[PDB]
Image: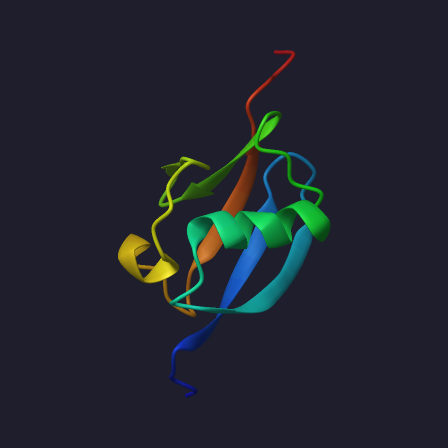
Length: 86
């Protein structure tokens, strides 16, 4: 029911099964800044892990805004590993 330039995006760790909060972020937030938050809270590391949306990779070098990625308050973002043992 709530609409606006601030949206709640849910984060989940495909590696561990952990479910992080819907974090209140803005359409105007850069992709790089979203990852900057994920580094602090989710312990994300762009060298060991990748951020996924629509099951494809969001390159950590994209300086685009969440708005340009088409993200909304109903979206799920996944943390998936770059390295796998099997």
